[PDB]
Length: 315
Length: 313
Ligand SMILES: *C/C=C1/C(=C/c2[nH]c(/C=C3[NH+]=C(/C=C4\NC(=O)C(C=C)=C4C)C(C)=C\3CCC(=O)O)c(CCC(=O)O)c2C)NC(=O)[C@H]1C
Ligand SMILES: *C/C=C1/C(=C/c2[nH]c(/C=C3[NH+]=C(/C=C4\NC(=O)C(C=C)=C4C)C(C)=C\3CCC(=O)O)c(CCC(=O)O)c2C)NC(=O)[C@H]1C
Image 1 (cartoon, rainbow over the protein chains, first blue to last red):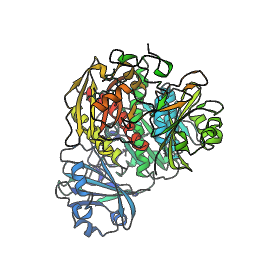
Image 2 (tube, protein in one colour):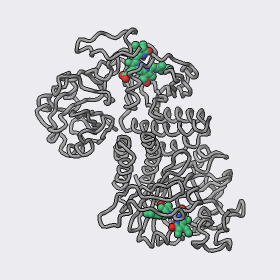
Image 3 (cartoon, each protein chain N blue to C red):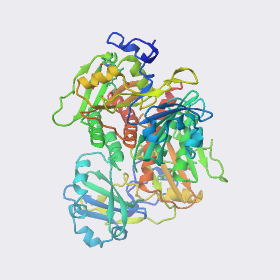
Image 4 (cartoon, chains in turn orange, cyan):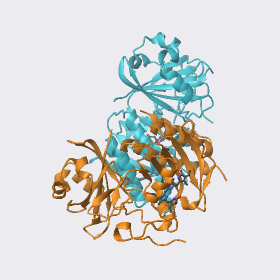
């Protein structure tokens, strides 16, 4: 039965059990994963409102100094570019990316998107023809099976992940592993099917709009935003569009129990519906840098197109 | 059918026999790169472009005996695996060579039956592609998508004019969006007859998705031999971007005052929906890595055109 979200934990909401799965407001956890930092800022003035508690250590500045400046002063070269790329009223799915040379922290990748009157800024550390070669190989795959196999093998070669599966949704939202590339010694998940509650309904809706999400370390504690609520609204900060957003504790226990240290997945979206997932596992924690993740994002789109094409060749 | 090419004493091309020019077998290439053909098994260099000596820095005869194994040691096994016998002519493999004579070359290979076609071009060596991809996806409708696409391509390439040219059901073409330098004529809204892009050229554009003319006044460079030794027949060059452009179509560019021209197929439901069409007033060799960006954009636009057309119908 579909039911509306509970309030999050920090607003006195209940703790999540197997009973109330579909009602966890996973998009507003009030916290991020510790391998990057996040700031929120007023979309018109550029006043800095919220920051992750670890921000001082990524950005090399005291909180009170950060919060006391506008983005115009903090990001003089990027602030006008942000404002042109992310105009008021734009969708929350639109992202702008730049690379910064920050004194204390080396090269940072900056990813920005806009939710209403809020700008959300994510900072992460950042670092030949493999993509072009893959694009052509995907297109020349003769059928859906060969496409799925080429796609899994390519992603594994690009990333070094221990296990890469193509996980396809059935009409009842159960899912099945239809191809996989895996490290020697791992047991096969090929042909196994998994029940529709394994990836509940509010996560599938979110995965149709925001196409990549990850868990770099399944044992890492989440880092709170400070303050936790958006001071504009005294309400929760929407993080569904932020790759740094903390992962559901329910989902992290599910991965730990499987022996997974690091998890990543790309959505494959066909005709406006979530067709499947490029799902990756690593046994140890593992951070895939932003520019490599971009390659996977591009492959997500290519695969969406090629899945349509291969399936049309099939009636 | 097709007329024989000129160099096999076929008729010269007019506006009476527009549909019958064998644009895939011109026997020559554009001079900003070099092409070798080679045997699929032996790696034996069978044809070369008369200009190969320039790019490769090799005494002419040296090449036309040697083997790819010898000539490209690191690459030759990769090719063997990447382009297995029986693969499609559409499948391409690329690498960057740090080659003694020329700082860096791009190498592009595909296979047509028993022949490997190798293309060499100068090359080199950020977020504009990722930023463009998200911009295309958030365009609210087909019109805005067209506008974003043309603007994005112009910004990435510096081309004087970028158009989105859409085919009607009878192959009548219409410029539905345009991004252009100040002080050019506007081709926005204009329609053009179907024979401007003749049937045999639309079929080729459905399979091989990027073509260009780097300099509309440059002479083609012959293949030597012109005929493939294997077959004593013309080498198919339809999947080669270095392939010489139809003199008929270069005359049409010169008469417009274009000095360089590039397009990308937008393919939807197995059919040619439209072209990303680019103009430069002067000669312009777009480097291979930037062309790759446009090739990606072509696929992304193909996806988004279907998405956007579905939310009208
Ligand atoms: C009562 C709650 C439960 C629950 C919640 C939940 N699950 C996700 C997301 C995912 N669950 C996945 C499950 C699988 N992993 C596999 O390897 C297989 C099969 C081989 C299955 C079925 C997957 C793949 C995802 C997507 C993310 C990923 O790829 O790692 C969420 C949302 C997480 C978030 O967005 O932060 C939630 C809340 N899952 C259950 O099984 C029950 C106990
Ligand atoms: C007797 C045959 C004729 C003919 C042949 C021909 N045309 C092409 C390719 C193209 N023609 C194009 C025409 C236009 N360019 C524009 O900018 C506009 C309008 C604003 C039109 C109508 C285009 C866009 C192409 C595609 C290639 C490109 O982007 O430059 C070929 C194929 C050449 C090749 O692939 O090597 C041929 C044989 N064109 C005619 O107009 C008649 C006279």
